[PDB]
Image (cartoon, rainbow over all chains, first blue to last red; front, side, top):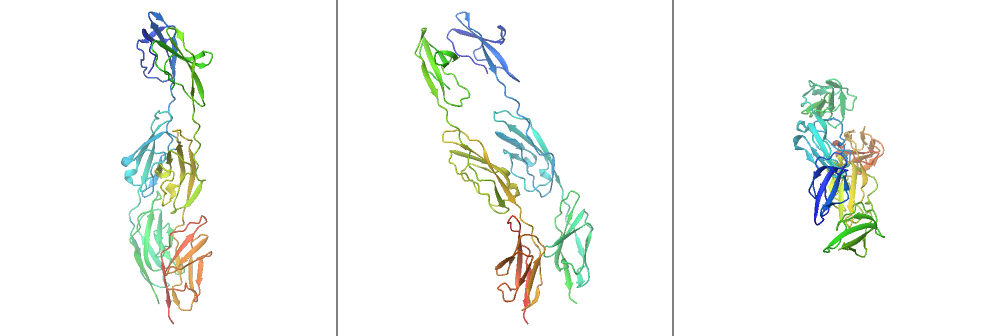
Length: 231
Length: 231
């Protein structure tokens, strides 16, 4: 909007060109549309028939708010957490995304249990210190599925001194075998042999978790009892 | 904003220089932009063609609100609490940080279970008693990870009078061994030997916790039974 002071007996005229030509409005306080850069307007006031000196104005145009900075497209495993953030400072942040994710923060509340419904594209827009809105910038999040619960078979009726052999049919890159006392071991193969001299040669309830190509750990298997008998 | 009283038949002129030169506006109530310190303006009113005495004004500028005082960068262990506060008095406080932390208090609600998602930079800004905003000041919080659950092996089939020997493979600075009745002991070594004359020579379910370099205590191990038999 442009403006001019009130003068009794005055008529007003605004021009877009010094030299008093290319008139644009005969209102006192006319508007200007679509400003993209700094521009000037000229006011010439005429009271009783005499024109005044020409009085120019400059409308200063605030620069473009730059796009918000986001993490590159990332990848979480189901069960992990999606921590979004932006490195840029703003008066106001506006985030939106999958599953209705909505927030007003530089560092939004972390999604604590990633699942398939939280995968997708998360978008951020920013309001600068001057009031101008930035263009939207977004990050894609892929959530990698975990393997299903493995099944485990053991040679459970063991006489002490005989090897303990545990095996699965589950498929993954690596297998995590967990002892009754919490000790574990990771194997590349589906079959684990425990030698009587090992700290893992123990009776009780054993479990298996399987790790896939994406590095996701399956739910643990239903424990299988191992019984090591005396001689 | 500047102002002047209404006088019938008057025109108004404001000057930035006593001596009646460097005119700045012919409005009654013009504005002043970007004041950084105290400044004066001069009003000269002219009704019927006669100028008035020059009447000066002084615009007083309120000092800068100083930066809020925060704790130095600190460090919590996972499971401990992050207690933020500021020592300065204000009309309004505005805190923000990791995990969406937001508050309006001199002493914000304490984060009661520190974890990795609460680590990061916490920022505070202040509004003074006069309405002026301070510059942002921040404190970084590092949350130190606890060790994983230890595994424990004991020589459980013990004849009374024989030593009780307990050991782990877990790594840390110190090991906390906890007796069935709650009594405990801390060792530098991974192996604990309990002499029959000790108050710790007791049967039941024993556990182990391990302490790392940062001083964090691991989750306790799965209890191992110890059985001390009579002769």
